[PDB]
Amino acid sequence: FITRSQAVRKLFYYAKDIQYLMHKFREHKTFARKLTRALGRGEVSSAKRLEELDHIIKERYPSFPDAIRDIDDALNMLFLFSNLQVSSKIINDAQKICNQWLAYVAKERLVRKVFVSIKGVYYQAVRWLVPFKFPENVDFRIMLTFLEFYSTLLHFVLYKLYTDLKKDKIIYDSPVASLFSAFVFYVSREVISEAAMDSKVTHQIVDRPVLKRTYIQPQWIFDCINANKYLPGEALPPHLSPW
Amino acid sequence: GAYKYLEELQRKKQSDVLRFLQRVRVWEYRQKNVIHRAARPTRPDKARRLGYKAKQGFVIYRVRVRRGRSLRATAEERVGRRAANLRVLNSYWVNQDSTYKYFEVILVDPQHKAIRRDARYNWICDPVHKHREARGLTATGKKSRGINKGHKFNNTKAGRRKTWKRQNTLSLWRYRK
Amino acid sequence: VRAESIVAKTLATSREKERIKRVSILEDKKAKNETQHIASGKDFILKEKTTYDGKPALLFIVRVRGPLAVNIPNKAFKILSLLRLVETVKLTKNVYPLLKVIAPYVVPSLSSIRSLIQKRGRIIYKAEPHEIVLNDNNIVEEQLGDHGIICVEDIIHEIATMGESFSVCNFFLVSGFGSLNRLRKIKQREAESNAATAPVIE
Amino acid sequence: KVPPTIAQFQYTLDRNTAAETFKLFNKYRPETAAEKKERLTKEAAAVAASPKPYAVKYGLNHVVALIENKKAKLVLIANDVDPIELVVFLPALCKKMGVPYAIVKGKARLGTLVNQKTSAVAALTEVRDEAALAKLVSTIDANFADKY
Amino acid sequence: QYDLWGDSTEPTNEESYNPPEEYLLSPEEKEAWEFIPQKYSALRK
RNA sequence: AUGGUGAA
RNA sequence: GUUCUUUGUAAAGUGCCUUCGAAGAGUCGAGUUGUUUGGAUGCAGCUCUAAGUGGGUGGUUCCAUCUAAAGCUAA
RNA sequence: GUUUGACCUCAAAUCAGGUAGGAGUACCCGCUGAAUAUCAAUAAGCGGAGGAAAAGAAACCAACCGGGAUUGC
């Protein structure tokens, strides 16, 4: 059998399924030398003129349901980058993709399980994870390529899902959907949000020791998904993982 | 134009500047193969007046021939044999020394579409021009053949063999004269 | 090193020093309200031209890192050291005369402010110079909870709002090389490119 | 040790004045093929009174045509031309015509500023900036002709 | 932007922020551990 | 005489 | 013959006036050595190597005729 | 700059688009070539083309009141 290094150089694996697989990344290398030539010439107009994975997605995932196999890692990487030498535009695009996915999920409310953990707030639709909104204290090139591939896959996934503006300046099927319906919550500094300040609500959410719209903690919602025992200031239950 | 200055400078062949240039160039060529592709002619005026043009289709070759079938004819034959797909148009002297004499020959490729579509150069694409040096149709070949006008070339004006055949034939008409 | 660099440095320093001197003289004369020998007695700020309202508005500060040829003067050095903006308060009547001086060396909504605060996350902590990250909210409570800050979100809200943590927190809180990165920098140079009486440029 | 007509090269404009000359010449870069094509297309679309353009003269035959007419004010000559005979006489022609000349190392460097891979010579006839050209000519003269 | 597929035929480890004290590893065993469940007052802390 | 053949 | 197109301040020609007005170098040529001619010519190794109102071919002071050292072209 | 670019030169690719050998040979072109004058620029040999080939529009012929590409009779 051809060794991995030997097969890569020619292009342990089966030669039968690898030899035929030998068939723009290589051609892009010419752009570097063209840019160097333009820089040497000392004129930028030619450089501007020179400046002016769908195929792999289908073979890897011939059908939309097959995407679920890698959707775990895809969402993990996308959410990790959404909160993270990656360019700022890449971070913005990753954040936008995650926000669109969350908005679509909320539109259908296709959520079944949740678990707040030290690593992050776990979720289930398929399981996915997002870290906290805090700064994160390795070769990012691999991470960049993985992010690009996962974003390309998620673009088609979101297109399929959707087929089937001053807020930007501020930012039945299951018990989760059945429960909390019409229960308009009010969230304090820790549905209407107090952060926007910078009533028809039936419940109010606040975790501070001192308080003045029933006072409930998010642990109530978490446990119900997974004010009986969640009044403000009281000890919360063990919060065991639903899985 | 500058080409007049180049011609005038080349007129004084024995000038110390041209002596230095020639001795440098011969030494440089001595480290190269007998026949090799030349990037550009070393005598642009001579090539230009010989019909060479800097366009896709023309090729310049430098060939070395032993001193002492003229040397230019031998060089043309060698370049034609090596450059079978190209047609030899003309050649000019570029250097000499006690051991070797160097000539530059310009060739035109009839296969290149540039030459084929060139109204001023597509004539060489005709099959009758194949291996011009072989039949002595080049400038050096014609000169060696004695082709010219006047009494000095009466016996070799056009064909040294043809006149012998003409003067050896016995023309007989239907009605004898 | 060739004399051209030092010559250019001296010329730029002299020009910018004269520019700052005229600004300081104009501000001093305006403080006296003797609008009889100055081009403009009022104040302006440029986004377009906008009048400088007396309201102490708070806006983010950005560093432009230049003009490079202008060696920073002593006054600008001290102003940047006090504001620790040398590395690459509010808009009050007493702060404007000093902000205008460093105007050539320097230049929001809840969405931008919250992200900036939650991403940069500088926290002076005890080695002594530790400033790593907003590690835990309990750190803010221990170091700053006495002022009514139970978490960094309180600091964000009080910065967005006209609170006291906006002032208190001051004591608590294309960029590449290679051929490929030269064209982007050259393009950005066009956006990268000042009268004393002119309005402040934002 | 070579004939005096040779070795006039290898003595060239200093780094500072050469850089100044290159900076001055870069201002008059001729309109490249793409720029000229797009400008002509724009003009045709607008059609579907004009000032004389300014650019550097670099063609050896064209430059020699401008030289000996006394129109050329400053000429740059490459010192690495393989057919040295093409440029051996140019300095003498310029001296006879009283046209200041400057030898700049590198034909490739000379051509890089005229949108060409290589350029044997470059000359300026018209100017936008005359004081700068005169100062550069005086500096080149004092640093090259009076020295060598 | 297009339907490239159409019709076709082809876990946590109890690391909660407020877990039972038994889950939390003892300080002595933390040396041998060289993610751990930890006890916190609430989500904000 | 010209050009080839085989033969130690 | 029949039918669509031209165009673009596009390209040429005629007579006049006016200002200018380039020309194939290791080439011609002489020497010598091999070669051809019934021609003394030409061909060929090599020392040297020509000028621009210049050069080549012919005769009694020169007068007659062309502008070589590039190439294409049916009968 | 204890670097990064402009070219120029030289190699390689089962690279893309192309051409060259050789055959025939009465005629054509060149080289060579026997049995000091004669058989002889023949015989034989080698190389290069077409239906024809070569040559071809004078540094020509003439010494005339001049003719004006080459080729054949």
Image (cartoon, coloured by chain):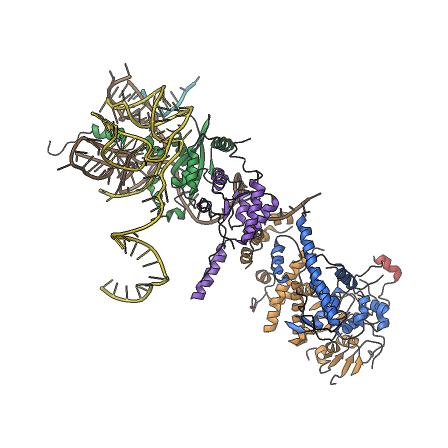
Chain colours: A orange, B green, C blue, D purple, E red, F cyan, G yellow, H brown
Residue C187 sits in quarter:
bottom right
Q: Residue at x 51, y 51 (%)?
A: D115
Question: As drawn, is A83 to the left or to the right of B10?
Answer: right
Is A226 drawn above or below residue D105 in the view shown? Answer: below
In the picture as drawn, the residue positioned furthest to the bottom comes out as A200
In the picture as drawn, the residue positioned furthest to the front comes out as C36
Residue A241 sits in quarter:
bottom right
Q: Would residue A209 be visible to someone looking at this image?
A: yes
- Residue B27 lies, in percent from the top left, at 51, 31
Task: Using the image as rendered, state which of residue D85 and residue F4 is in the foreground.
Answer: D85
- Residue B64 lies, in percent from the top left, at 45, 31
Question: As drawn, is A51 to the left or to the right of H57?
Answer: right
Residue H49 sits in quarter:
top left
Question: As drawn, is B108 to the left or to the right of E7?
Answer: left
Q: Would residue C202 be visible to someone looking at this image?
A: no
Task: Using the image as rendered, state which of residue G36 and residue B104 is in the foreground.
Answer: B104
Task: Using the image as rendered, state which of residue G43 and residue D99 is in the foreground.
Answer: D99
Instruction: Give the quarter of the figure containing the N terminus of chain B.
Output: top left
Task: Using the image as rendered, state which of residue B163 and residue B172 is in the foreground.
Answer: B163
- Residue A72 lies, in percent from the top left, at 68, 65
